[PDB]
Length: 231
Ligand SMILES: CCCCCCCCCCCCC/C=C/[C@@H](O)[C@H](CO)NC(=O)CCCCCCCCCCCCCCC
Image (spheres, rainbow, N blue to C red):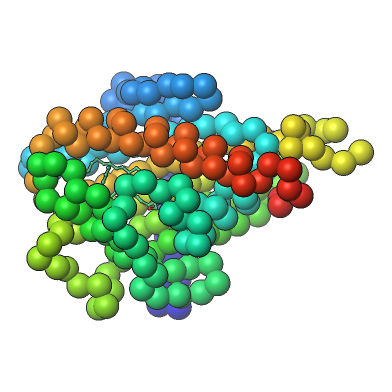
């Protein structure tokens, strides 16, 4: 499909940069910590527009990276966990693992409602060596599409989001979900697409990202509990 090169560039950039430890960078601040979930943000505002890169890490017992990515990507289960949208639909299927999605978000007062149009791709990155972890990644990044032009009711946000998963399995005869731990890195780089009050945007991000990470990961645990493991 026409976006294959763009997908590869986006995936490679995440694998090169998004897994780099930000812990030693004074510009990256821990904003939320609960259990194994840590949420960090770098405050960035250019021409009044809040761009604050967000990075979270989590460690989720009893689920695999393949499972987590499947649930994050699969549009059929989207409304079971997502809480920030008014509607979404699939604009185009590019491949078995790549779709283009249009969605409108819930309005955050006092700003205009935001919409987004993004390619969502799920990819397995095989281990190259014995000690290299296998990675499952979902990348959601803005693309243009003639069937979803700009409209007069919403401001079009631009996003680059990834959910990046590596799975640790402890030696057991068969593997139990008690033996598996999914290490998650989630990154979100969002351009709100126009002015919005900085304090409001930052408060909403601080609330909504951990709320999502907790809700979504608990959902995957709930939906996979008692079921055969999909590695
Ligand atoms: C009632 C709350 C309404 C919030 C509306 C925020 C609109 C901001 C622009 C779009 C944000 C992109 C969210 C990414 C979505 C997809 O990758 C995916 C599937 O939907 N979900 C997540 O990654 C899970 C993402 C969950 C967290 C999203 C919260 C973002 C808040 C940002 C700060 C407020 C921005 C409002 C602009 C005026």
